[PDB]
Structures are given as C-alpha cells and as structure tokens.
Image (tube, coloured by chain):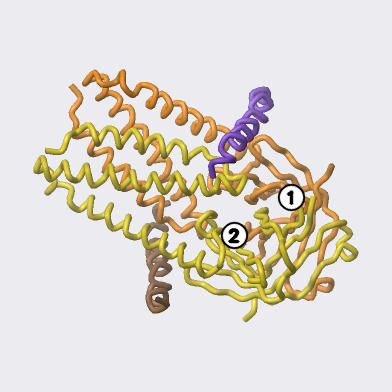
Chain colours: A yellow, B purple, C orange, D brown
C-alpha cells in the first residue's frame, strides 16, 4: 500500500526546484555550481516522482496502459545519465571542474605546469581568439573568463563529446599592433 | 516601460550580494 | 471532486519533457527553438501539475500545512514569467529572435540597413573580437556564428537585462597583419 | 573506455540528420 500523499509532496518539491533552476543568474562561478546542484537535486526528484507514480500504476493495475511511456522516460533518463558520465569523463580529461559547471557544447583547453585552462566554447571554428588583460589578469574567450596563472601554450586544443581538435598559434596581437592598451590577443588556427 | 527596468535594475544584484554575504562561509 | 489520475498523467508527461529537454544538443539553430519550445511545454506542464496538486490539497483539507511552499512556487513562477517578458522585450529591442533562443547572459548587437546581428555573449568585457570568414561568410564570436549579410558598423553595442554597453571599433586585423588567410578580426573597445 | 566513445561518436549525428530529414517539411 503506497500512499498517494508522497506523490503530491514530490510534485511540490520538484516544482520548487524547477522554479529555482529556471531563474538562477549564470554570472559568477558559485552560481553555476548552484545552478548545477539544484538540477542534480531536481533530477533525483524527477526520478522520485516518476517511479513512485509508476509504483502507483502497478498498484492500481493501470500500468498496462502506459508502460511504453514510462519505458521512454527511463530510456531518456539513461541517456541523460550517460551524458553526465561523459561530462565527468571530460572534466577528468580536461583536468578542471569547468565541464560539469558550464553547459557549452565544446571546451577549448590547454595544460600548463601548474594550472590547466578549460574555457567553454560553442563550436569548432577556423580561428580562436583569446584576450589577456586585467582591470585581475585573466584570459577571456567569448565572454567566458578564467583567471590566468601562467602563459599561453602555442598548442591549444578543443575538447568535445567526441571531438579533439588541435589548434596552432599563428600570431600574437600586442597592444602596439592593435592600439588597445592592456589587452593582448592570441589567435589560433585549426590544424588540419 | 523603462521606469520598471530602472527600478528593478540594481535590486537583483543587491539580493545576489546579500546571498554572497550569507552563504560565503557555508560553501 | 478532482480525480487523482490527472495528477499522475501530468507527472508522467512532465517527466517526459524534462527528459527531452535535458538531452537536446544545442548545435544547430532549429534545435534551440525546439530546446526552448519543449521547455515552454514543460513550463505549462509544470503549472498544470502544480495547481492541480494544490487543488487536491484544498480538496483534502491538507492545504493549511504547505500554503507557504505553494506560495513560494507561485512567486518563483511569477519571477520566471517576468524574466520571459524581459527576454521578449530584449528580442523586440534587438530586432532578432536570438534572445529567445540562446540562454546567454548578454547579447552583443549591431543594426544594419537590412539585417540586424544579435550574437550571444557571456559578460561585458574590455574588448570584443569578431571573426569574419567562410568555409559560408559569417561573423563568429565565442563560437556563436551568424551568417553575415552586410558589413560591420564601427559602433557595436551589448544588450543585457539591465545594461546597454556601447563599444568602439579600434582596429581591424586583416589577413596580412595576422597571417591567417580568409579570416578578418574586428576588435572593439568598451566606451567609457 | 575509448571503444565505446568511438562506437557512439557518429550515431548521434546520424540520428540528428535523420531528424533533419523527417521534420524539415514540418517547421
């Protein structure tokens, strides 16, 4: 005998967590983790409200009607879990926690002696531009900024779910060439 | 329509800074 | 008399739509709309599963226990709706459908005679780099690409929820300066 | 571990292209 109140409680909590994740501003680094963390809790809630509801359908005998729908739900949950495992594999591979935080498709990366830079990126392009500067010294790509702790390697690489695209450093645009004070531009070209 | 935008501009940032102050020692 | 089966049906459908939105790849433009559209449906479902559950609590008289929780849910839904209205105001202001599609914090924009460019961006930076090139002619910022239909204006602006930051075109890095063939770099500096 | 990645690489893109073909005339 599974009481129906737990389903309502799970529904209310899941609504709370959807409402929280749908309004969190993605400005600072701490929010992103929060923005991820809430989702994680939500996912658990999304599981808890699902199987319990399924446990009701078998309890009421109304499970033969929508077994396909719940099978689809479980299949998509398995796909999402595999996606999370791939993200964990990427962040282990990129030596940083950025892949779990940011939701970008790709991650341009380069490893130094002490620090490893893993900056999110939309898609593989012919060229990649990195802007080094301060107000704090940092490297910025497409708005995403990472506090620099060392120089830039002439081989930068873009990680992906299934792509590993190396890039070649061609030119470094110093302030004299560009005319913009306190801003260094590094340009990388996609190696064939 | 811009009056509401001007009023609502910095209140969200102030709330986020309050959250910063509250949960800084928690994480 | 509100039957309890509708709550289970809404739960199942909401789980389906969470599962769909949590796996959609954000590579092409059509997916983004889909990725948004599903969310829209989900939001309706998130409403439908909520109030109905609330309608059960008043039906069972167990509403006095968690009125605060549902009030919080409704308050957060109101905040999310206001956020969507601000996004609609932005896309009306930016003359493009990109703000409703992309989830970036800011949008760098510039208006031409025939076409209007509204490219997503993370945060306001000192400089902004735009890469013009083909394989198709387009302007690319931080991986996000938009098919170019005209030139670039020397005044580019960044839209935001509450920020309107103008930028000044300082230098144009042509292929001779950079050494990268078929790639033009436009550099904008933030006006004070 | 890389064998699964190699196997799963292009199947997702092929499925997305199938979706492209199916729903191109719908939107």
C-alpha span from label 2 to label 1:
16 Å
Residue C190: percent from the left, percent from the top?
A: 80, 47
- Chain bearing tag 2 is A
Above or below, comparing residue C190 to residue C50 in the picture: below
Give the position of the C terminus of chain A as an image quadrant.
bottom right
Asked whether residue C183 appears in the rendered view, the answer is: yes
The residue shown at (68%, 59%) is: A141
In the orientation shown, which residue stands out farthest toward the front?
Answer: B25
Q: Is residue C111 left or right of residue A16?
A: right
Tell me, for residue A120, which label it has, or none: 2
User: Under tag 2, what secondary structure?
Assistant: strand
Nearest the camera: C189 or A85? A85
Residue A162: percent from the left, percent from the top?
A: 48, 71
- Chain bearing tag 1 is C
Q: Which residue is mark 1?
A: C125
Give the position of the N terminus of chain A as an image quadrant.
top left
């Amino acid at each position: 005998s599974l009481p129906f109140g737990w389903l309502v409680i799970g529904v209310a909590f899941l609504a709370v967590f959807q409402s929280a994740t749908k309004i969190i501003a993605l400005n600072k680094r701490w929010q992103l983790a929060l923005y991820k963390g809430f989702q994680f809790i939500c996912n658990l809630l999304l599981l808890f409200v699902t199987i319990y509801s399924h446990l009701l359908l078998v309890a009421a005998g109304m499970e033969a009607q929508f077994l396909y729908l719940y099978a689809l739900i479980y299949f998509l949950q398995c796909i999402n879990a595999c996606r999370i495992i791939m993200r964990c594999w990427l962040c282990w591979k990129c030596k940083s926690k950025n892949p779990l935080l940011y939701d970008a498709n790709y991650f341009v990366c380069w490893h130094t002696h002490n620090y490893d830079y893993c900056i999110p990126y939309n898609s593989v392009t012919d060229t990649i531009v990195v802007t080094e500067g301060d107000g704090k010294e940092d490297y910025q790509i497409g708005g995403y900024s990472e506090d620099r702790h060392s120089g830039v390697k002439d081989y930068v690489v873009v990680h992906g779910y299934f792509t590993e695209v190396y890039y070649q450093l061609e030119s470094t645009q110093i302030t004299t060439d560009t005319g913009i004070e306190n801003a260094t531009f590094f340009i990388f070209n996609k190696l064939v | 329509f811009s009056k509401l935008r001007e009023q609502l501009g910095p209140v969200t940032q102030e709330f986020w800074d309050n959250l910063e102050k509250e949960t800084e020692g928690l994480r």
